Amino acid sequence: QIVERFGFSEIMRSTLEKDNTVGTDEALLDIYRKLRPGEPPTKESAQTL
Amino acid sequence: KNWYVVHTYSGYENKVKANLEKRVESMGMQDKIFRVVVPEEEETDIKNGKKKVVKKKVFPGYVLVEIVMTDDSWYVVRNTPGVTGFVGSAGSGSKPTPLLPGEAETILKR
Amino acid sequence: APVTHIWYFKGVPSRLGYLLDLAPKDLEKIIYFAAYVITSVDEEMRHNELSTLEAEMAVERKAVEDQRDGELEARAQKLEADLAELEAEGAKADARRKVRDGGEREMRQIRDRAQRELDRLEDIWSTFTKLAPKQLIVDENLYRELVDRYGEYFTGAMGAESIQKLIENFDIDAEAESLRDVIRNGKGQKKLRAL
Amino acid sequence: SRMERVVRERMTTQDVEAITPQTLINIRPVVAAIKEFFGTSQLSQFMDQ
Amino acid sequence: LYRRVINRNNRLKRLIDLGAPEIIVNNEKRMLQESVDALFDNGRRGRP
DNA sequence: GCTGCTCTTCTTTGCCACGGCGACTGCCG
RNA sequence: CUUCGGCAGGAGAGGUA
DNA sequence: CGGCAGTCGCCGTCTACCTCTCCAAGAGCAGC
């Protein structure tokens, strides 16, 4: 869906290519870890945040 | 599952003590939080009359709590009327440093 | 207990890390009770007890292999027993393959546990092999084991008293002449740092 | 919002069948905030006459 | 600021004189260092 | 159980320009 | 020659040249 | 190993004068 809708400009498709993120799990955890360094990486408190 | 140190206020050790209990009953934490012994000193205040012997905290500001793990525990014990935080930030606090394997008895005995 | 003046630690540049050759982050960790530091070492006992130490370690190391193969074999035995009961023919070999793979996986995790053990022991060893003054240890378990088993003939602490002990043994002349030599010969950013 | 915290805290300390609305409300923060705003503030000013 | 310094110094002194575990005295020493730093230059590190 | 004296301040929501210079620190090559 | 006895820090807002 | 470039943290930002108001609280612990 993201590549069907947000795909009329090379900006979006090029940012999509170099994303390196695949899986809402991986993504969510990446941001969870990012926000606060060195913290308990429980997915419950991630969806909470 | 072992013992942990908790920081209170100077003047709220027994209010915290009572609160932790009342809260352990007014929430539903009888399968998590366990005994909460604030180290006490029964130093007989000799008076030959009206006696003024009291708790006279040995560690003004700290209260020892025997709890379980997880995070709910943490939240309930920290958000109590009269506490200041935890004790054990010897490296991020990820694994809150517990009292050395054999150290509880050295306080509970006396 | 001793403390530290804020002017000579939090300034730019930090006049304490310029003297002890420590990064200011390490100073912030040591002073505010967040990491241990190695105040002094002694290579006398170290070199005069290498063989002995290594041998004693190896002796404890062998126990791991012992237990390892003990459970390994006992597993193999019971596994092949239940294979003779219901895996030699097509009685119920369907999920019996998974059954015996159960204990094969438990033997794989037995090897993973021998890995874990030998690994952490290797850590301890490599640590005690280097042990140089002014080296930070961030993990509490490593330092606790080091001071429990190899505590003597080595010292470490944390706080402002540790900084005081580090300054106590500091030899000004040697560091001054080393800096002057680096300035005289040797190019790059080392020139600027030595200046 | 300040008084709500005391109201919420007081529910885990008293006992049911003894909890009364006149026992959970502390009206001190509200009057303190009102008095602090109407005096000693940057927008309530001494009148020009 | 002098009052805070004296308070945490007499607390640390009593804890030490009785013989408390290492973690409590370490926390007290950290707090005393922070108080002294606030006395000399308030706001340099952390919150004022 | 009276009122004056005395002592003390950490989770939980608050938080709010612009140029110059130098240290530094992961980070790529 | 005159015995005791009697004071003045911060924060905010608005103005003048 | 060896450059290296973004980034962040600390420094500075005109002189003299006049008028007004406001400056912790909450909870525990006495000696009767």
Image (cartoon, coloured by chain):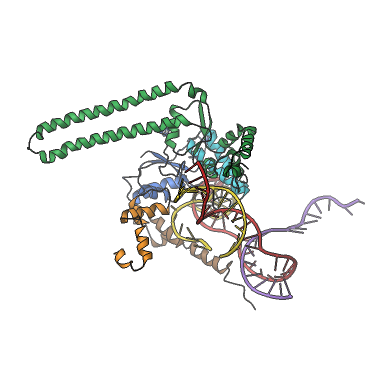
Chain colours: A orange, B blue, C green, D brown, E cyan, F yellow, G purple, H red
Q: As rendered, which of B41 and D46 lies closer to the eye?
A: D46
Q: Quadrant of residue C58?
A: top left
Considering only vertical position in the picture, is H30 above or below C78?
below
Q: How many marks?
A: 0
The location of residue F3, given as percent across then percent down, is 55, 55
Res B53 visible: no
Instruction: Give left or right: position of C174 versus H7.
Output: right
Q: Residue, x 17% and y 30% (percent of image)?
A: C78
The location of residue C147, given as percent across then percent down, is 46, 30
The quadrant of the image that shows the C terminus of chain B is top left
Q: As rendered, which of C41 and E39 lies closer to the eye?
A: C41
The quadrant of the image that shows the N terminus of chain B is top left
Q: Residue, x 39% and y 22% (percent of image)?
A: C55
Q: Residue, x 61% and y 32% (percent of image)?
A: C168
Considering only vertical position in the picture, is A35 above or below C169?
below
Res C123 visible: yes
The location of residue C50, given as percent across then percent down, is 45, 23
Q: As rendered, which of C118 and B110 lies closer to the eye?
A: C118
The residue furthest bottom is D49
The location of residue E9, given as percent across then percent down, is 58, 41
Considering only vertical position in the picture, is H8 above or below C155?
below
